[PDB]
Length: 93
Image (cartoon, rainbow, N blue to C red; front, side, top):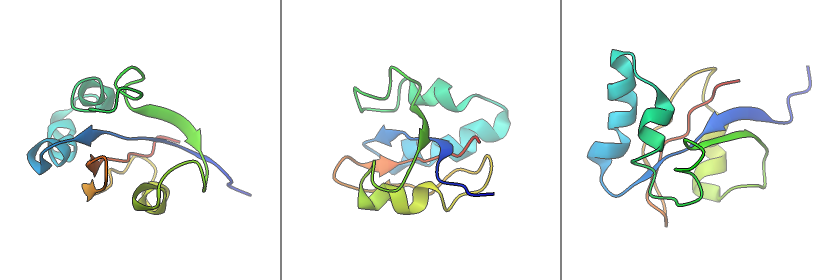
């Protein structure tokens, strides 16, 4: 059907070793929020485990929204280096 919005998260870091670790750490069987509540330097994200819930095109930045919905159901996005840093978008649906 018509998919306007979708569930996804986000995590901001200062080093790629941290952002990229979001796809490696969880690989063991951890929780995304477990890293979003720490790594996420964004004051307005670490409080919600980087879980922004449902979003759409126009509620985020270019270097984020683009690869924010291009992911699959439960897939992690690459460390997109932006003005805020590496963005780790992860869909949850």
